[PDB]
Image (cartoon, rainbow, N blue to C red):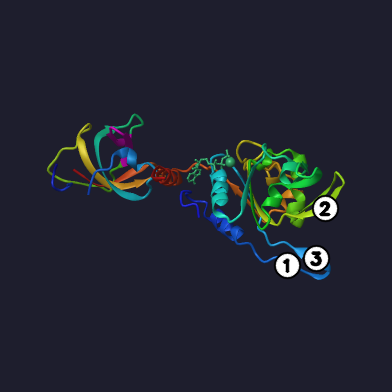
Amino acid sequence: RNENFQMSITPIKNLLGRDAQNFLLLGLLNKNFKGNWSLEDPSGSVEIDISQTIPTQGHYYVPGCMVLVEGIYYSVGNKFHVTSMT
Amino acid sequence: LAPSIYGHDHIKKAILLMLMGGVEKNLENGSHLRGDINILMVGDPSTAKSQLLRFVLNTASLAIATTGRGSSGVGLTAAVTTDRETGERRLEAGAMVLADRGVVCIDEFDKMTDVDRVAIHEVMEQQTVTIAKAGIHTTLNARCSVIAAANPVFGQYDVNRDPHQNIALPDSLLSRFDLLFVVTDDINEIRDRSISEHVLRT
Ligand SMILES: Nc1ncnc2c1ncn2[C@@H]1O[C@H](COP(=O)(O)OP(=O)(O)NP(=O)(O)O)[C@@H](O)[C@H]1O
Ligand SMILES: [Mg+2]
């Protein structure tokens, strides 16, 4: 319902195999059992790299928080490299 | 060609050139060089080999469909029958003769019994079939592009082993095909995503 979106969210399961391409996610901020940070969606989950990200500053980012995320999906490590988070 | 088949670009290129085969040569003493292009697709299951045969069957001006088990060697070349109109022994054209100046499609080609494949050789080598039975001693024209589909001796292609060990057919038959294509359903997320979304659109 927010005007900024009506780019648009792709559910996480849509990413799989869509290599090296920009996407916007909405997801539950998990920490996977393997230890890596991750996002989850009703359709699935994906591990994320935050090492180059820029969050918006007016927020906390605790686990389990619903976060909008922009990034590039990379199939080689099955990672999602996060541009920014909000 | 075959817009409902993803990928297989080099095969569709070869199919196009096979629909448009090169000029046949005739030389001294009536010596002959064939102009058909003979294609064998051998490979993993579910790699559109049969669908490509069915597209060719729907696209060539003159195409005859066959399948390995369903084809007799006699049913392929020509068969003797009595013409009940008169009572005389007469030849009935088989698939290779009916496809003359056309193409033949063969699905499940490696499933043929070898007394069927023994009858393939003259069509490939000489574009003709020879009859020497029932007091009928003749030679018939069978000038056509064979395109065939097969699987390896194992259910899928085994890259650990040589083509002559993967492929059931004799080298005395494989050497007669113009292009021997090996295809595989080799798993890859990007290609699987692409082929999948194409097939869903289809
Ligand atoms: N690249 C492709 N694009 C679209 N559909 C495909 C593709 N590859 C396979 N298929 C589908 O797979 C199904 C089986 O195709 P088919 O031509 O019978 O495979 P095949 O190579 O002959 N397998 P087999 O007869 O067991 O050796 C068909 O419904 C095709 O539509
Ligand atoms: Mg087949």
Compute the Cα span from label 2 to label 1: 23 Å
**Mark number, residue B101:** none
Q: Is residue A40 above or below residue B95?
A: above
Q: Let me know if marks 3 and 1 both belong to one chain.
A: yes
In the picture, the quarter occupied by the C terminus of chain B is top left
- The amino acid on which the numbered mark 1 sits, given as a three-letter code, is Lys
* Mark 2 secondary-structure assignment: strand
Q: Is mark 3 within 8 Å of ligand 2?
A: no
Q: Residue at x 25, y 37 (%)?
A: A27
Q: Residue at x 47, y 43 (%)?
A: B188
Q: Position of residue B39 (x, y in %)?
A: 64, 53
Q: Which residues are magenta?
A: A36-48
N-terminal of the pair, mark 2 or mark 1, is 1
**Mark number, residue B31:** 3
Q: Residues within 10 Å of mark 2 (few under 14, many from 20)?
A: few
**Mark number, residue B138:** 2
Q: Is residue B104 above or below residue A33?
A: below
- The amino acid on which the numbered mark 2 sits, given as a three-letter code, is Thr
Q: Position of residue B179 (x, y in %)?
A: 65, 55
**Mark number, residue B25:** 1
> Magenta part mainly helix, strand or loop?
strand
